[PDB]
Every structure is written in C-alpha cells, then in structure tokens.
Amino acid sequence: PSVSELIVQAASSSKERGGVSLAALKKALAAAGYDVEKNNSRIKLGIKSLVSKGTLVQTKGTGASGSFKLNKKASSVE
DNA sequence: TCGCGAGCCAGGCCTGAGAATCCGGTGCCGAGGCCGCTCAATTGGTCGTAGACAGCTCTAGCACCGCTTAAACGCACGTACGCGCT
C-alpha cells in the first residue's frame, strides 16, 4: 500500500469534525504498520502531493503541519 | 493492485586539506647554589595572674500522661501545561 493510499484510507477512516492532523495521521500510519520515523519525509511529501492534487483539502494549519480532510467532490471531477 | 522506468535519499568508500602532535636542535635567562652578615630566635631567670579544679545552688530540658481538633492523608477527577514535533 502506497503512502498516499494509506493516508486516504486513514483519513476516510477517522470521523473527526475538523479533520485529521499530522500527528493523527502519524498515529494512524504507525498503527498501520508503517514506520513513522524512518519515512517522515515521505509521509510529508505524500501529504503535500495529495493537497496539491486536490485529493486532501486542508482545513486547519498551513503546509504539512496542519489538518486535512477528504474532498468528496474532486473524486468525480476527473 | 501490478509492471516497470527512473529519480531521490542513507549510508559507506575514499581522499584531500587543515590542524594537532611528536621529534629534533639552539640558545637564553631564570632556578638553584654559595658566601657574608646581622638580627632575630633561643635560653635562663623572675614574677604576677588566667584559669583548672572542687563545690554548691537551682533553672530548665527531658520524660511522661491525657484530651482536643487541626491538619495530614488517601482517593478520585478533571484539565491545562509540559513535551514532542514540525
């Protein structure tokens, strides 16, 4: 499972009203068997790529350190 | 979700450059020794008194008891602040 796929799965899995933060996504990936320490840069890059592609809409914070949600709209505007 | 192309990061390899450090020799001036003296440390004596010892008086420091209740305590719960990470 690619980093972005696990990120999307965890984000759709969590039911936070305000979104899933960097710490929350790290905890989810760590619970998913992912090394959150050795691959931190990759997690951040995947998050940024998902934000840029419009897959994840950032709700709080700026950059990688904020919180993000699934965009249920861009999934059908391909 | 897989095949596969190619690029990015982790770490090892290896060397260069710069600096620390050991090795050698020269010289140079301050440490150690010696001589002269002189003054201060020693000895002996006297003498007066500072304090060591013995004794008594009597304060207060210790030990004990009981009653009261102020406070220490253990528990449970909540949150806000320290810590980690970016």
Image (spheres, coloured by chain):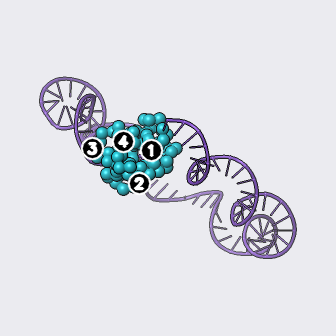
What chain is tagged by disc 2?
A
Both marks 3 and 4 on one chain: yes
Mark 1 — residue?
A4
Q: Which badge, 2 or 1, comes first in the chain's sequence?
A: 1
What chain is tagged by disc 4?
A
Q: Amino acid at mark 4?
A: Ala
Q: Are marks 3 and 4 in contact (CB under 8 Å)?
A: no
Mark 3 — residue?
A17
In the rendered view, does B3 fall on the left or right side of A20? right
Mark 4 — residue?
A11
What chain is tagged by disc 3?
A
Crowd class of label 4 (few under 14; some 14 to 19; many from 20; radius 10 Å) = many
Distance of mark 3 from mark 4, alpha carbons?
11 Å
Crowd class of label 2 (few under 14; some 14 to 19; many from 20; radius 10 Å) = few
Crowd class of label 1 (few under 14; some 14 to 19; many from 20; radius 10 Å) = some
The quarter of the displayed image where residue B44 is located? bottom right
Mark 2 — residue?
A52
What chain is tagged by disc 1?
A
In the rendered view, does B41 fall on the left or right side of B86? right
